Length: 150
Length: 150
Length: 8
Length: 8
Ligand SMILES: [Cl-]
Ligand SMILES: [Cl-]
Image (cartoon, rainbow over all chains, first blue to last red; front, side):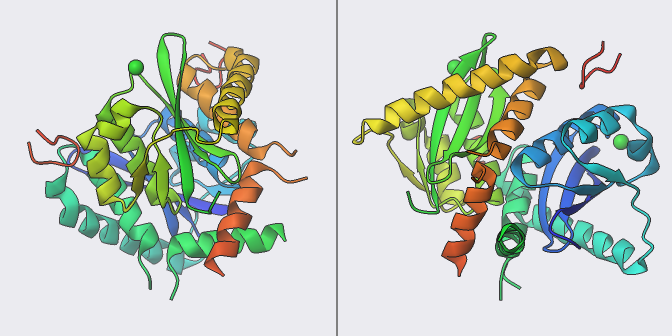
C-alpha cells in the first residue's frame, strides 16, 4: 500500500462487465462499463488511469490480463510495473469482495435514476469516493500522494 | 483559481470532438473523444469528472451546454455550480487556445502509435499531466487540493 | 423518460 | 497492426 499501488477488479451486472481500479492505500476507485473484459479494453482503461493519477504498480485482476501482450504494451507505454494479483495476503481477497458488494448495493440504490448502467456506475463511483467513514477515499488519496510528492 | 474550479473546452480533430476539462489553478486536464458535443455527452463527462476530483464549479464551454437541462441535471446531481464561460479575463480565451494547440501538437507526436484517436488523446492527456515546467500539472493539482483539505 | 441521462 | 491499441 504505497502511494502508487493500484488493484484491478472485474465484476459483472446486467450481463455487462464493470472494470474497477482501486487505489489500495485509500480505497478510492475509478470504474467503467465494457461489454466484456478483453486485453484491449483493459489496456485502454489503464492508459486512462495512469494519465490521471501517478500509477506505479498495477496488480492485475486475473492471469489473462497479466499475460495479455496488449495490457503489457500499455503498462510499458505508461510506465507502470505490471504485477500479478495473488492475495499473498488473504485479507486482499475479502476486501475486494466486499467492495464489489458495496458498489453493487450503491448501484441498486441509484439504478432507477439512470436509463443506462454506465450512468449508474459513475453515480456509484461518486458516492463511494465521497463517503466519509473521518475522511473520504477521495480525501485520503490526495493526502497520500501529496505527502509522497513533499 | 480556487481548488474546486474547472473549465470545459471542446476542440475538433479528424471529424471528431475532443471534450476537455481543465483544472484552472493547475492546468491538469481530463479529456475524451465523442462523435459530437451533445448535452447528454457533456453531462456524462461531468458526472465522471466529479466522482474523481472535488469539482465545485464548472465554467461551461458554450451557451448550448450552459442552457442544456441534461447538463444542469448532472451538475445538480453531482453538486456542481454550473457557470457561464465568459472570459471577463481575456487571458482566459488565450490560455485555452494555446492548450488546444499544445494538445493537438502532442496528439500529432503520438498519432502514429495508435490505431484509434481515443488512444492518442489519452496518450496526450498523460504527457500533458506529467510534463514538468519544477512541478507537473498532476503534482500541482494534488498539492492544491491537499492544501485545501488541511 | 424521467432519468438523469434521459430527461425525456 | 503495430499499434499500442492494435498489436496486429
Ligand atoms: Cl468478460
Ligand atoms: Cl459537435
